[PDB]
Image (cartoon, coloured by chain):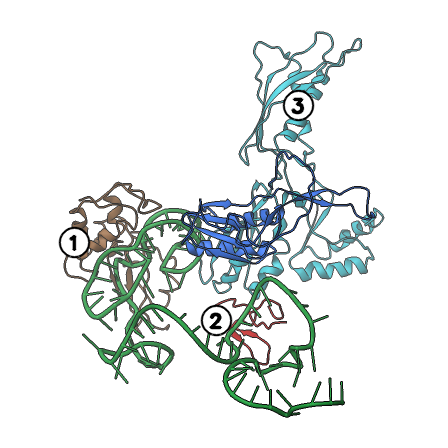
Amino acid sequence: KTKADQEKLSQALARLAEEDPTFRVSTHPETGQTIISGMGELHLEIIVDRLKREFKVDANVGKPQVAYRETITKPVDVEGKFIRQTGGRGQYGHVKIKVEPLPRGSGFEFVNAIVGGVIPKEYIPAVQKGIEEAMQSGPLIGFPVVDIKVTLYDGSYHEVDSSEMAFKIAGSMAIKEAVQKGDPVILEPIMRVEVTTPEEYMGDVIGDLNARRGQILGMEPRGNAQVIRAFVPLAEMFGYATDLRSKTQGRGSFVMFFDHYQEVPKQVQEKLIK
Amino acid sequence: MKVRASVKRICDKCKVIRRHGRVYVICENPKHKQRQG
Amino acid sequence: KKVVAVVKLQLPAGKATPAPPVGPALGQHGANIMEFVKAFNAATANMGDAIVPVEITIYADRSFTFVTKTPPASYLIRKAAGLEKGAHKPGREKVGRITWEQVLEIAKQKMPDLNTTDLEAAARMIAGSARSMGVEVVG
Amino acid sequence: MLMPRRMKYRKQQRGRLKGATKGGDYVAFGDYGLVALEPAWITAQQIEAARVAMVRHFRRGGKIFIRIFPDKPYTKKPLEVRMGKGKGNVEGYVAVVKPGRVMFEVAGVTEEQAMEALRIAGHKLPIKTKIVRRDAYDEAQ
RNA sequence: CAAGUCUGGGCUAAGUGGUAAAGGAUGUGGCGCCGCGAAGACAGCCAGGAGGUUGGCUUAGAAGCAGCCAUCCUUUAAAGA
């Protein structure tokens, strides 16, 4: 809750983490919020009493967030101009680039596409720190615009006006628009899961998984059990413990691993614009 | 599909009954149990 | 001490590992799950691939048994046309073919399984399986 | 939607809907048809709404023939305004339909499919309708 | 409340009559045309209801039974890819 209680909580674990190492407290290193590792609904639940009562902290209990990503569909190419000739530090930076989407899981790639050198040598690092920068806050919501290849294939400059910095903008302008133009697309996190389950409960097991935006990959049996592998979205994945152990009266266990990122079904496009 | 103004046959197992000046329509799936009104 | 059987598995050629459906269903068999990848791949060392149906039957003394049929009628027919897949849409699209004789040669391959005891009939079951995968019969 | 592109007069008088049809009471094109049983005013939307659902119903179908054509401006004074002051502005358009008039008709499609599509069209319309085949529609030149 | 609880034939079973629409319905009468007809029909009982073949494509998997096509053969008294 208000930063006030942020403290009562600190001590909360500072003593509760000695009095029970069967959990783990983690501050999401990308976005404040802290995760509370538990070992079952009830578990986290009963901590919610003690930690909220015998410690009288009264905070929030919703769910983890999802590491989205931004990017684009169609490749574009725009002008990146900047120039400000008034009288001196002219501030003069201007480039044109080549933006092209890359396969979901391609990475980050620039292209020093300049002929003889209409774009000076010494100014590129900064033209990139510019582009690289701007990829931070997505065009859609604000998240790491990824999976693209950038090509610097022109750009002039000024003898006295340009600056290392002036390019960092120009370049951070050409990028701040290529993305806006090439129709953004909300990528999202997919996981790898494997429920260990007696093909008894299976039946619904897979169903359940299907009606979770997820799509199966297989089930090569084991012992009296049978394993099921497949991908799912972290959003439509929550609180799976007391969902699996449900459809299995307890004889059910799973794992989870990250894998790739992937576009949202448009229905989920305008959903996220909230 | 209980009460309505357009009662029809929602699957082969359904039957258009009419006990009591009231056209009922019954089937094996208690969902199709209708009745005009 | 499990119950009895006329198990109707369907194991391909070669892949004979105790792993299911050869474990759950031959877990009430006592089935020497390894006296197959030798007694099988011995007879079907000939063929190579193609699935081979099998009926492993258990008893009470906890022993097994099993007889195997022929490889799919659709098998011999893919290799006899440079085919692999059917033709996605049978009929309109021919991708390869078999003559009046090549079909009458395969009915020979699977004649001790079907039902009729000719070829004028047997062959028809293959010429039928022709358009089942869009493989017109040459004549 | 559909409508005149030009017009001598932006507005025209009411008039009244009588029996007969004057014409288009026969097939002549496709294979099956839909005809007006009561006289009325079909709005474009009314039409449109069907013609959509018409097509919708039968993915990859034939050709759909709209044999009618709206061309009577629909008038309407604004809301909360008294009488006089001239006439009323246009609202939309409508086609004066009369019974025996072949409204739409499909061509190339299984009867099972024609008998269906047409049926549904009838639902987006205000008036009761009949589906006619093609027997004696032979010669009406 | 004056003059037929008049006569012959038909319908209606809700008091419809005794004021409402699209749209629904094995309502109840009445005409029609057109098939099967005792070498056994309708309901009907017990029967058999198969083998190629899990058709081919597709799919995680489709085996008659998601969905595309395709719909031939078979042993028959008959059994649909």
State the CA–CA distance, disc 3 to disc 2.
66 Å
**Which chain appears brown?**
C
> Closer to us: mark 3 or mark 2?
2
- Farthest residue, direction top: A159
The kind of residue on which mark 1 rests is Lys
Side of C97 where C85 appears, left or right: right
Residue of label 3 = A174
As drawn, the label of residue B13 is 2
Q: Are marks 3 and 2 in contact (CB under 8 Å)?
A: no
User: Would you say residue A58 is visible in this rendering?
Assistant: yes
Q: Find chain A in the image and tell me its colour.
A: cyan
- Farthest residue, direction right: A4
Question: Do discs 2 and 1 share a chain?
Answer: no
Residue of label 1 = C108
The kind of residue on which mark 3 rests is Ala
Chain identity of mark 3: A
Question: Which of the 4 image quarters holds residue A76?
Answer: top right
> Closer to us: mark 2 or mark 1?
2
State the CA–CA distance, disc 1 to disc 3.
72 Å
**Which chain appears blue?**
D
User: What x and y, as percent, mark residue D54?
Assistant: 52, 50
Is disc 2 surrounded by few (<14), some (14 to 19) or many (20+) residues within 10 Å?
few
Chain identity of mark 2: B
User: What x and y, as percent, mark residue A186?
Assistant: 62, 39
Side of E12 where A90 appears, left or right: right
Question: Do discs 1 and 3 share a chain?
Answer: no
Is disc 1 surrounded by few (<14), some (14 to 19) or many (20+) residues within 10 Å?
few
The kind of residue on which mark 2 rests is Lys
Q: For the residue labelled by badge 2, is the local secondary structure a helix, a strand or a loop? A: loop
B7 or D25, nearer to the observer? D25
Instruction: Tell me how many marks there are.
Output: 3
